Length: 152
Length: 146
Image 1 (tube, each protein chain N blue to C red):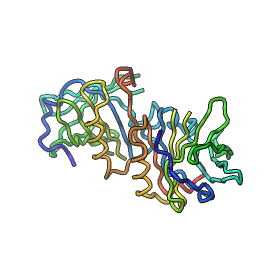
Image 2: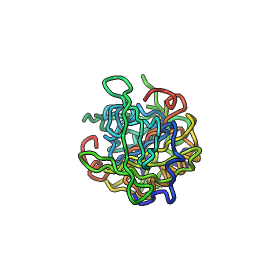
Image 3: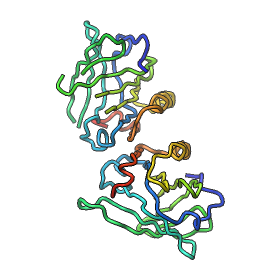
Image 4: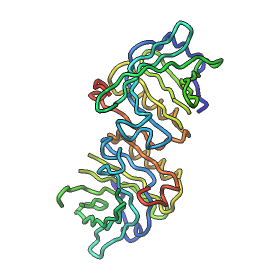
């Protein structure tokens, strides 16, 4: 992954979002409701220090569990580091702030198309497909408006 | 949009499932999902039907798709699916769909990633209600049930 957003201002991404589409380097990252990269973004919360907190939903033991991840700022404004056993980077590819945001979790690679409103946005999905060009993706999922409003 | 003038003697032989897509995530998500089937071979029958030799999670299955009045449209009796051949160049790639829900595949003649085949599959899928897409590496193409 090399296309990160030039000039990102995370103070303009705060609020509630919907995971519209998802793609991963391995089928087993996304295939099951319980698969590792199968996490729905509920909220983005930039911190005053310029870190990016994610509020996630995960299907866990047959219900929808909430999880908080803190992605710490780096020298590069569109690149954040998650403290974990192995370094996990968050790469923000693109956003127009008002409608859609595209990002990737990189160890294995899992990317998402987020939208502000729970409707299918064909422009956002076209931009997601362009940004995914040449990434080693083996699985892609997209959700209908019904699924966007449902827990997980 | 089905393959005009399909020649079933020319599609005969060995194939590999390179990519697949489906209208519903649950048709392809699990190794045992209903549309999760790997095409190993197509044979014509003398009656002009098309035999598919498939692997499914790893069981082998032989399915006869009966000709219909429409060229390149076959039928496979209890859970009736139409088989729609979208396009093939015979020598490299074949694109087809199972329609009741819709599950489509990109087949290639050799167990290698083919740029043209995947581009033609993506084009064909552009105006279809797909919600899941899978692609396999060459290692998986040579293995039982990928």
